Amino acid sequence: LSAASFQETTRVLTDAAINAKSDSLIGLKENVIIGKLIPAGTGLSRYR
DNA sequence: AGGCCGCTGCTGCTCAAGAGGGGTTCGCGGGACGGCATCGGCCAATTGGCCCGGTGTGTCGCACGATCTGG
């Protein structure tokens, strides 16, 4: 997801489709894209 | 003379023209049917008038009369 949103979307998507890659949503960009709490600052589970 | 190991040039991807025939729609009307909507009566029913008939208790309109403050 992050690689596709950076640049060269077509190549990244056609490479990820063949390998059947699974995204675990650990970064900041993916959490921003799907619309949930980023895993930093006040979005950590230690504080909430 | 074929196979193969590199070079080297080239290219590509990405960031800034009528006519006939037939089933179907809808669109007007067109009226028929059934239905619910609108108008003289109407009497004896709860509330609320509207009073008789007793006093009393308590406000108000005024008489006798004492105390007190000012004049």
Image: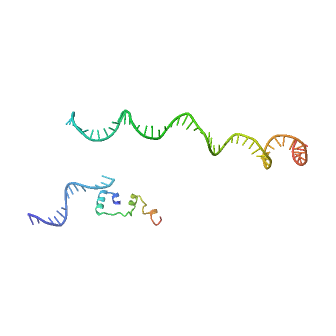
x 39%, y 58%: residue:
A34
Q: Residue at x 45, y 62 (%)?
A: A43
Along the line of sight, which residue is nearer the eye, A5 or B20?
A: B20
What residue is drawn where x is 38% and y is 60%?
A30
Asked if A17 appears above or below B39 in the picture, the reply is: below
Q: Nearer the viewer, residue B16 or B36?
A: B36
- Can you give x and y, in whole percent of width and height, for residue B35 in the image? 45, 41
Question: Residue A36 vs residue B46: left or right?
Answer: left
State whether residue B56 is above or below residue B30.
below
> Which residue occupies 31% across, 57% down?
A9
* Total count of labels: 0
Left or right of B61 on screen, residue A39: left
Nearest the eye: B2 or B66: B66
User: Within the image, what quadrant is residue B29 found in?
Assistant: top left
Judging depth in this view, the residue of B54 and A41 nearest the camera is B54
**Residue B23 on image: x %, y %:** 26, 41
- In the displayed structure, does residue A42 sit left or right of residue A2? right
B40 left or right, relative to B55:
left
Q: Position of residue B22 (x, y in %)?
A: 24, 39
Which image quarter holds the N terminus of chain A?
Answer: bottom left
